[PDB]
Image: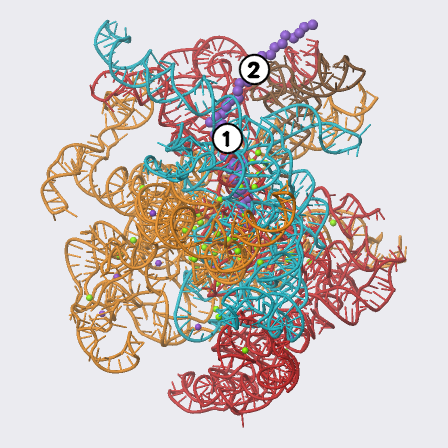
Chain colours: A purple, B orange, C cyan, D red, E brown
Amino acid sequence: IGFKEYHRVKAKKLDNQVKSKMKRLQNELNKHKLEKPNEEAAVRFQFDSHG
RNA sequence: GACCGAUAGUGAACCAGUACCGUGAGGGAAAGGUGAAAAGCACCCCGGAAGGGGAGUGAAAGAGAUCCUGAAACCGUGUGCCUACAAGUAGUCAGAGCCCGUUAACGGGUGAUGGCGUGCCUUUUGUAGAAUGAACCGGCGAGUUACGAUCCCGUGCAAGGUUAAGCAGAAGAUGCGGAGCCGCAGCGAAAGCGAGUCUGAAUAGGGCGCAUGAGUACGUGGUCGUAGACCCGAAACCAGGUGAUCUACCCAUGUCCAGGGUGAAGUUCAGGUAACACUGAAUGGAGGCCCGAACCCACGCACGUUGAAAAGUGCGGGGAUGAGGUGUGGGUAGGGGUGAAAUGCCAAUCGAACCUGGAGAUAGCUGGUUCUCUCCGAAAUAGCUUUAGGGCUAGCCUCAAGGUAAGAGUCUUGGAGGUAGAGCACUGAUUGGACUAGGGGCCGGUUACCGAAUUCAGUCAAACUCCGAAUGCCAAUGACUUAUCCUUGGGAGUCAGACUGCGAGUGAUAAGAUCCGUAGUCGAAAGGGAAACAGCCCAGACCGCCAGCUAAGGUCCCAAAGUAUACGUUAAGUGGAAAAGGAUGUGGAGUUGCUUAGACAACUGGUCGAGUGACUCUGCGCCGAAAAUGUACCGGGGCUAAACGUAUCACCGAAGCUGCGGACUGUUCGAACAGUGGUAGGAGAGCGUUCUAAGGGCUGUGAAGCCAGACCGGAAGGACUGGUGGAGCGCUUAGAAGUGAGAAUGCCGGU
RNA sequence: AAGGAACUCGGCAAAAUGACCCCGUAACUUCGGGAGAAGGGGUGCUCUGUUAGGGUGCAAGCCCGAGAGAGCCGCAGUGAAUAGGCCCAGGCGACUGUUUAGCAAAAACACAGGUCUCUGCGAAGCCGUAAGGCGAAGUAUAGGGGCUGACGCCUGCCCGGUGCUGGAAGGUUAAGAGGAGCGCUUAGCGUAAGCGAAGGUGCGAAUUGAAGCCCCAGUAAACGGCGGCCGUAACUAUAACGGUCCUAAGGUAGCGAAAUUCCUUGUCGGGUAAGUUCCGACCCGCACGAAAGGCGCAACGAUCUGGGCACUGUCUCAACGAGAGACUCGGUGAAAUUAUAGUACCUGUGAAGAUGCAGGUUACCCGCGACAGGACGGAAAGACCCCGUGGAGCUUUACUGCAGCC
RNA sequence: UGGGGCGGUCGCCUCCUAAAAGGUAACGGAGGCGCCCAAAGGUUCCCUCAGAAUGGUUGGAAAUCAUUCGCAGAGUGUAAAGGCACAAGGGAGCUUGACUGCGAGACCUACAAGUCGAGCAGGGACGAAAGUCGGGCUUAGUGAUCCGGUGGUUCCGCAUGGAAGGGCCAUCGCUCAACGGAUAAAAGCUACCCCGGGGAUAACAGGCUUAUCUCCCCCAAGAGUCCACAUCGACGGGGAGGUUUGGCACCUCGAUGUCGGCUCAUCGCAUCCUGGGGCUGUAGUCAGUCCCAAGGGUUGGGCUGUUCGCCCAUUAAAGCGGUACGCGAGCUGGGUUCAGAACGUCGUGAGACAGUUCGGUCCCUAUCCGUCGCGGGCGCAGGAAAUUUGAGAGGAGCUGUCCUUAGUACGAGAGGACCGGGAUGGACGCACCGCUGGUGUACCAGUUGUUCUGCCAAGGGCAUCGCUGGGUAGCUAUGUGCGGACGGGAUAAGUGCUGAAAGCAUCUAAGCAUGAAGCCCCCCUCAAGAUGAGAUUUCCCAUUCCGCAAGGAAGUAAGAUCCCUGAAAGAUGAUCAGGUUGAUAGGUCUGAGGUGGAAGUGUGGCGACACAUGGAGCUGACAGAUACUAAUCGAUCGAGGACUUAAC
RNA sequence: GCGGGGUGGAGCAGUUCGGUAGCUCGUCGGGCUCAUAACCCGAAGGUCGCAGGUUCAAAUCCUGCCCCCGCAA
Ligand SMILES: [K+]
Ligand SMILES: [K+]
Ligand SMILES: [K+]
Ligand SMILES: [K+]
Ligand SMILES: [K+]
Ligand SMILES: [K+]
Ligand SMILES: [K+]
Ligand SMILES: [K+]
Ligand SMILES: [K+]
Ligand SMILES: [K+]
Ligand SMILES: [Mg+2]
Ligand SMILES: [Mg+2]
Ligand SMILES: [Mg+2]
Ligand SMILES: [Mg+2]
Ligand SMILES: [Mg+2]
Ligand SMILES: [Mg+2]
Ligand SMILES: [Mg+2]
Ligand SMILES: [Mg+2]
Ligand SMILES: [Mg+2]
Ligand SMILES: [Mg+2]
Ligand SMILES: [Mg+2]
Ligand SMILES: [Mg+2]
Ligand SMILES: [Mg+2]
Ligand SMILES: [Mg+2]
Ligand SMILES: [Mg+2]
Ligand SMILES: [Mg+2]
Ligand SMILES: [Mg+2]
Ligand SMILES: [Mg+2]
Ligand SMILES: [Mg+2]
Ligand SMILES: [Mg+2]
Ligand SMILES: [Mg+2]
Ligand SMILES: [Mg+2]
Ligand SMILES: [Mg+2]
Ligand SMILES: [Mg+2]
Ligand SMILES: [Mg+2]
Ligand SMILES: [Mg+2]
Ligand SMILES: [Mg+2]
Ligand SMILES: [Mg+2]
Ligand SMILES: [Mg+2]
Ligand SMILES: [Mg+2]
Ligand SMILES: [Mg+2]
Ligand SMILES: [Mg+2]
Ligand SMILES: [Mg+2]
Ligand SMILES: [Mg+2]
Ligand SMILES: [Mg+2]
Ligand SMILES: [Mg+2]
Ligand SMILES: [Mg+2]
Ligand SMILES: [Mg+2]
Ligand SMILES: [Mg+2]
Ligand SMILES: [Mg+2]
Ligand SMILES: [Mg+2]
Ligand SMILES: [Mg+2]
Ligand SMILES: [Mg+2]
Ligand SMILES: [Mg+2]
Ligand SMILES: [Mg+2]
Ligand SMILES: [Mg+2]
Ligand SMILES: [Mg+2]
Ligand SMILES: [Mg+2]
Ligand SMILES: [Mg+2]
Ligand SMILES: [Mg+2]
Ligand SMILES: [Mg+2]
Ligand SMILES: [Mg+2]
Ligand SMILES: [Mg+2]
């Protein structure tokens, strides 16, 4: 009696860890989320050589 | 004093802040009554005494010291009826026999036997429930009060109504007191304007108002707000204190450890060396050393487990000169201390001690909430919700006041719509044939090699439609019938629903499953049937009757009524449990092959001598058919009808309906008609308890209380008589409430 | 009796061992131990005997006292009571010690030893608001804190992240200093519109202004971390070797199916007739690893684990006996529980598991000694699960704060 | 929220579910939206689309033309539905009505909101005019309040004038997307845990269902040398059971204790063994499959907590299930899920498991029914003492090996029977103590320590009965004897005989047999409360009172009890042997069995000790005898026999 | 069913935000050497897994389809 409930209670604890990790990560990003630094564009043009 | 009267009122009426409980702060009871007067039972008898039986005192001793009254539980004694073949929610209805004789009544007690019948409460869709609560009896124990708001009702005055504090006065009535409050005027955010005003450019429209008018003061009642706010109940939080006489650690000063063993360093001697080293003996007496009592500890097992003991005993076990045991006196205190660290320990309490206070913390949760009858009578739904077992608005109920006839049923007529069915005209899916562009595999020419598209026929669709109902829905006009309906306001409860039939989804076209639509019953519905069986069938209990007719369902016995009538079927106890499938079971229709030119069968083409084969539909049966305590799907007996089908007629059968009698409610005009189940809940009318006022009484020639009884009223309830009791108590009208108990693992007492 | 662990989760419990003397005693070792290892033998009484010898004493005489020989008795001589069972092997902890008073004594805590770090003395650290204290009447060979835990051999790589330490300029930043300016107000100017001094007043920018942070180095017995893919050797198979990607760096020694191995009762060897346990190896380490230390390890342990011997009522399989209860009599006399009970069985029905309902079956009335199938028995308003916009303890880069510190 | 969690969802639009008005749920089936357009809006005017065939330079299936056919097969910004070809689809001219104030009246609706709207006024666009225009073919494209920003303003301005500040109108700021929005501001652990509730809600067992599971079938492609159906049974189809995995959430949260084991069983049959049969690809021995059959039986160990499973060794066999996965007020407590601790792993962490490991309190005196035993009462038409019948109930029910038949039948051999006789075991049961043993606490003996009887000798107490060696009665198994034997009756499956219906055939319809360890008996035990109270033999005898009777009372008869001595009986009652003309118990005497040579004395020895007297002495329960002691005297209870009929 | 990958021969970027297809090694050809390696000089090798859309332009954005790898299975 209560076999699966016991094991499923354990499962629910693992879920709570995921939810907490998620929530904290989201909150941390909102507090401090550096944007990716500018990737300077590269001008490219070549005077193709003639014969 | 419309305050209490010994469980009340102070905790304390009494030698009570006592007894008792706690180390302490602190907590904290129980317990009143002789008589007018002790006149408190001289004397005698039984007894060791207690306790009795007389005799005396007294109005009374059945007033004799827990001494007014003396209920119930509970415990006994005697006996009028019944009881040892009986299956019991304990009664109720019927009923002999026996025994009595009353509030004199179509009486009382008991009860062989027959019928019927699973407590009360709470909580539930649903409880006899094996869900909850109560051992029993008694007492106590829960919507109250203050101040505001609003509505109804009553009264006074009325376009007005009314005073508050305060001052005089019986703690009163009343007089004075007009400040203030509400209303008569509204509109606008406001300036402001005013029967109008605001918006707007507007004499427009529209909103809110006016014309269509009643308020106010006080009282009663309903509800609401703020207060503990109907009563009981947390785990907790915070504040101030009390604890280290237990236990943790520390500090100071004491004290305890029977006996035995092992033999460290060092030292000495002897040997040894050039010297040392080295070797052997002896001495020596180290150690969180060894073995083992006291003492301390607590490893295993048994026992104990309403214990001898709220942690022990018995048999073994570990340490036992050490980081040892223990005494005395001290220290550290809870947002703290102490911890060789277990969240362990800090007075049998520790993830935050104990006591008191804030405090009646809060509890959308559980439990409880006390007299009676009558009128009406739900909901378990929608929306929103840090919402889902809560709440709010609507729906559904009730009361009152208005409108009033505006409601409803049916018929007739009109209309909106795309479901069932059907259909392929579109969109998808799809079968066969034809015709086929191409596509691939073969040498640009072909394969029956994939094949687009076209066409012919043929299927199919919740999210296909050229079509398209039945019902249901919205209206209109009459007619016939019925009595509802709407507006405003007061009060609610309900938001867990259940099953059954039908139409669907989810599921597996399972579920007493789940979610909607629709109708019913239950919930909140007793009675009859289905053996028992909320939801199925029949049918709605105001009450009495030893009257009648019926419904579902029945009629051989249990058990009321047909062993009814007529015609067939079944042989399986089918009826009284299930499929695919199998089968010369049997009944009834129909078709067809052959047949006295002689069949089928059997006999060596003939003998023989009247039937013989196949198939379709259909009624009732058969096999397929094995579960666990015990026949075990007919309720039982039992049944060959007492089963099944068809038809007919009788009778039985409810609390349905009818007849007779009574009560009440409503409607219309004392009559008639109609109605009278009920949970949550609304409304009305009453009974009873305590106290007050005013009248009128009762009571020592016996009050209240208590105990009986066969009386009275529709209920709550009220009398009368007798016994006990020994001094208070009813009745009528009105008023005010500590006003009604069977349940709260309620509190206290008794048993 | 016979058997002897066949019992059982497990030799739990009991049995067996036990004193003194003599002989004898292994692996291993930290050279002390292990060790009472283990395994054996002896034990009574009598006579040689106030013994050989020893203590006391002036001596007599008192005590102590081995060893033998020679005999006697019994089933048996520490004749009773009291007094280790032992051996082999492994895991963990070194050890003695300490711990959940009252379900855990242990591998947990402590420990000596190791290391890191703080502290120059009014030390750091700690208690307190402060004074005043502990530290300490101490002074870096001392004191506090963290981690590890005797001893032996060792303790590898990574400073990118986080912490700590040290820097130097610079960037960012508060109060406080500064008050450019702007608004309001109004003497006055004006036909008005509007402008507007001074004063007052409401805002106020530049500039200035520390630590911290940013930045740069170091530090791992600081908190921590310690990888993927591809190819390659003349049988094959594996790769000493090579390529590339990523990282701060990719796990070294040692150990390994483990207190760690899910698959798994891995495979192999040993032990048994039979071994999911055990021991020895192997290494595809789900998910070892070097001071939350790695690997060994004598001694120690009421530690955990497996195997032998002894021994037995643990068992095959139960029997008998003793005492105390039970039972009868005399005395005394509770408790939990309890809606009232004249309180059967079967099948069924029902809130789906009935003493109580239905249909049958069975049953004369009342007890006593016994057993526990039922009364969903008693006890404790379930601790599991879910719910409540309940509580408390704890954690942190949750939110908001406070002390402390700079 | 078909427990919670994860996943998914949360507001709005379209369709289907939705049952032809509207509305209508589920974590039902499909999709879209959080915009876009300055023209893709308004108006005025004009206008048809897709596709196919044919003709044509590049040109190709498909670009552009041209003709014919061609209801929409197109398009309509953006999903779907409803519309649209007097277009809402395409093109062109001018413009901004994608206006301001509004708004009769309606739809929808709990509210808050949302939707439609003629018409009026102001000032405009297009148009010759009528007239149309308050965005788009229609239906999504959005967010309350509070609080801030901005613009306007015949509003207010706290003595007054200003101002500060506010109001009104317009407008902006929320993926407040959990979209009717808790605060401006918020994550976890609890195994150290606690409270209030719920069977409204998880689970076990129960109930319903039966997808799955187990078992059984239908069809028959086939496999099987041929041959579907000896055996096996593809592709499909139909059931039963309620042991499995599930679905549901109906009972239980003011408690229905768990897996495994132990003790004790009980039931079903889907039969593991034994019994009886059909078919066989059954020669014999063996087997295969199916039918009947539930009477009895159905092992001991190693490993593991285990169930299970593997293994070892047996057995005739090592059956499958139900009983709350039977059985914890019957036991155990090893596994698992309390508090401690540790490893691996995860986490910053408290801690946790996707894994392990060592240690960890099992309470209750039985009221009722039930079950096993034992009594008392009454009844059974007189009162007693014995012996009995059997309605009915319980018990028992198993089986191996060997010898013989017979090396026969059978077979090429190998091997090797049926049936019928006979012996002897295993397990199990009943009884009993003569035998073998156990026990034997009032028996006998040996012996240690100490204390006592004054000492010696001889003994007593205590030390587990001090210990040790024996042992009577009784009680006992492991010991012994015996049992399940012979068979009858009726049947099951099966085998048939005669025999029609249906000139044949046929076990069947009438009729007649056979045939199982099973059923009813036989065998053992209880049994007349069998209220239906039975039957037989024997004994006692009609009393005395009252009362009119019915009936009542009092002494007794036969007989029994109280009381007493006891055991062959026993918890107590009861039962049985006895109670003085009695051997009932004790004692006494004589024995048995048991122990094993007493004490005293003498002799031998220095002594411990040995020997003789002497199979001695001692001896609980056992046997026989014997009144020596106790069973005294007494008391109590116990019939006089109802009525009716029939036959005598 | 739920996720991750397919870029010259190997290992890897670039993909979100469209703009010449790349880095390291390797392969091939020619030198150097007696010859091989190293070294030096040139070149080839992917139209970004496949097939269609969108766009002036797609490895990159969209639609389908096929492989590889993890789990569950
Ligand atoms: K009183
Ligand atoms: K009461
Ligand atoms: K104190
Ligand atoms: K209800
Ligand atoms: K009187
Ligand atoms: K007694
Ligand atoms: K009954
Ligand atoms: K009951
Ligand atoms: K970690
Ligand atoms: K014997
Ligand atoms: Mg009082
Ligand atoms: Mg008086
Ligand atoms: Mg319920
Ligand atoms: Mg309850
Ligand atoms: Mg109760
Ligand atoms: Mg010591
Ligand atoms: Mg010791
Ligand atoms: Mg002491
Ligand atoms: Mg305590
Ligand atoms: Mg308060
Ligand atoms: Mg249809
Ligand atoms: Mg339902
Ligand atoms: Mg009811
Ligand atoms: Mg009625
Ligand atoms: Mg009639
Ligand atoms: Mg009748
Ligand atoms: Mg009637
Ligand atoms: Mg009626
Ligand atoms: Mg009251
Ligand atoms: Mg064993
Ligand atoms: Mg065993
Ligand atoms: Mg032991
Ligand atoms: Mg230790
Ligand atoms: Mg120790
Ligand atoms: Mg403890
Ligand atoms: Mg302990
Ligand atoms: Mg450590
Ligand atoms: Mg390191
Ligand atoms: Mg580690
Ligand atoms: Mg480390
Ligand atoms: Mg370590
Ligand atoms: Mg008793
Ligand atoms: Mg049922
Ligand atoms: Mg039942
Ligand atoms: Mg509860
Ligand atoms: Mg779910
Ligand atoms: Mg509709
Ligand atoms: Mg723990
Ligand atoms: Mg802990
Ligand atoms: Mg609780
Ligand atoms: Mg339920
Ligand atoms: Mg067949
Ligand atoms: Mg339900
Ligand atoms: Mg209960
Ligand atoms: Mg209980
Ligand atoms: Mg069978
Ligand atoms: Mg069980
Ligand atoms: Mg039980
Ligand atoms: Mg256990
Ligand atoms: Mg009972
Ligand atoms: Mg004998
Ligand atoms: Mg002597
Ligand atoms: Mg003594």
Residue at 69% from the left image edge and 5% from the top image edge: A51
Residue at 58% from the left image edge and 12% from the top image edge: A43
Residue A21 in sight in this render? yes
Q: Pick whichever, C299 or C311, lies toward us.
A: C299
Q: How many marks?
A: 2
Chain letter, disc 2 residue = A
Q: Please, what is the three-letter code of the amino acid marked with disc 1?
A: Leu
Q: Position of residue D534 (x, y in %)?
A: 57, 79
Which circle's residue, 1 or 2, is located before the other in the chain?
1
Q: Please say if D626 is above or below D322.
A: below
Q: Please, what is the three-letter code of the amino acid marked with disc 2?
A: Ala
Q: Position of residue B510 (x, y in %)?
A: 58, 45
Element type where label 1 sits in the image = helix
Residue at 49% from the left image edge and 25% from the top image edge: A33
The numbered mark at residue A25 is 1
The numbered mark at residue A41 is 2
Q: Is residue C189 left or right of residue C47?
A: left
Q: Is residue B580 left or right of residue D285?
A: left
Real-space CA distance between mark 1 and mark 2, rounded to the nearest whole angstrom: 32 Å
Chain letter, disc 1 residue = A
